[PDB]
Every structure is written in C-alpha cells, then in structure tokens.
Length: 117
Length: 117
Length: 117
Image 1 (cartoon, rainbow over the protein chains, first blue to last red):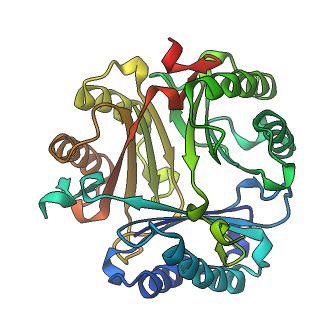
Image 2: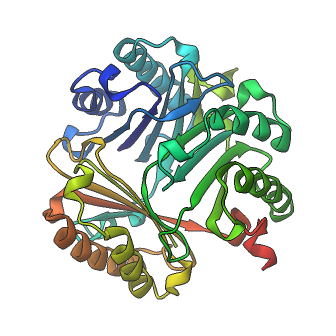
Image 3: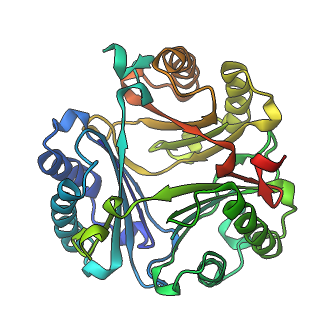
C-alpha cells in the first residue's frame, strides 16, 4: 500500500515516529505485510479543508485489490480516522481520505514492474 | 473538490492567504459549496515545468462529476489560469493543471465513505 | 510527462540540479521532447518505504500513451531505477515507482485543455 498524508500541522506538532506507527496500522487495517507498506508525511503545508484553514490532514491510500469498493473503504475509513484523530489531535471533521486502486503493471519495483515478480 | 498546488516559489513569495482565496475561487468555478472545497499548497519545491526551472506551479483538481470532460475542463482551466497567473505573478506558460474525476466510494469522510452519507 | 519525487533525504542531500537532470533523463526514457517534461521534487519528508524509515524515494510518472502497459513500464522502470540509484545514492530496494496514464482532456495548458491544442 502507498499512504500519503498532507497536513498543515507544523512538523513539530506531528508526533515523532508517526510514519512508523501509520505504517504498522496500515498493515493491520489493510491486511498486508508491513514490509509492503509505504508512508509519506508532508507537514507544514498551507491547507484549507472543508473551507477552513484550521488544522487538518488529508490522507491518500493506494493499493491493489483492497480499496476498490464502498463497503471495504467504509471499514478502512473508520480505522484510519480512529488512528489519525488520536495521533494528530484532530476531530473527524478535520480529516479526509481518498482511496485509489492500483494494478501491478503500475508498480515499478527493483527495476521492473510487480507484474514480473 | 480537492485541489493540490505544487510550486517552486518559496513560501515567502506565495501571497498570504492564497489557500483561502483559491478555496473560494474553486467553489465558484466548479459550482460547489465552499464547505466542500479542499486546498493544499506545497511551496519551496524543486521543479521543472516544460523543461525549465523558472518559477512555475502545478495544480491538480479532483472532484465528482464536474471534471470529466474536455469541454467542462476547458472552461475550468481558463478560470483557474486567470486566478493563478494573477496571484502568483506567473505567465500562462508557467502553470499546468491536471483534472481527476473521483467517485463517492473513494472519499472517506467522518469515518465512513461518501457513498453512505 | 509529469514526474513527482518524494524523498526523506534532506534537501541538502539531494544533489543540486537533480530536477534538471531528471527532466532530461525522462525525456530520453519516455521518448518525449524535453519541453514537455515536468518534474517536481519534494525533499525532507518523513517516509517509510517497505516498512523502513531508512533513506528512500518514491517516484510517480504520469503521461499520455507511454505508461500504460507492463512491458513499457518494465523498460521505463529499469532506466529510472538506474538514474535514481546513482543520483540519490540509494539501493534499488529503497525506490518505488508508480505509473499513471493520462488522457489529453485531463491536461490544462494555456487556459484550455490539450484536447484543443
């Protein structure tokens, strides 16, 4: 999985080691081995979420197979909201997630694509 | 809508409050309520646009329903170019936009997905 | 083409002028004129790749026509891995790429969309 988190929290208000805890949480939630989970955090950005520049965060989650239905994503969303609200000290109205299915021919890994591994 | 703006302008050359003005402009252009508009600005990046590292900006716009045709996007592009050229003091050859349709099952909101709200 | 590179290398460990060399490399690899190539580098991020927070980089490549098959992307991946491993002093296990086909109606250019140019 590929997780990307943009926030207007400054880096010094994003708890140390968030990327590592998010990586482990994602592995558990999405049912994927932790050595296949990728996390990118981009703090200190200028953001409006739902029209408001109060602290907020946007999460993007991309994966093969497991983020392509409403019913799967409803479950995933609940868990990721729980994780981020606590970590970032945000209410649920200050987080949004976007889910993006991927296919193996899209993933370049060790100089080839996942199709051939 | 979800707008993401990457620029090689340093943060101190991106006018204060851009994210708020872009949020209001997007609401007007895309015909969506301002409390559904999201904007993320990432300044100070290293960028080449059309082969050149002169100041520039890349905008991504994602939304349900309204960014999926050439004729819709032609109109949207004109307006967003007008907005950004003035705000960022850029010529039109230094901005590019990418439009991405989204579906409700992709949007995690308040711990569920938009499908169920 | 639109290339986006996220890294946890600090900006002062990303060689000067990387964005320019990546732009020229991409033009050669993807067979596109260099004045149509776009590169964005976002350094100093907090990242885990394959579960690990050691230095790493994620590259996204978006283009019309040339990134939509496994066999095309296998070739592209080899070249981009070669480029980035050397530039960033990373092993191949510390880089991942994602390929995203685009269509002309998605690209806002000079106030219109590529469809009409």
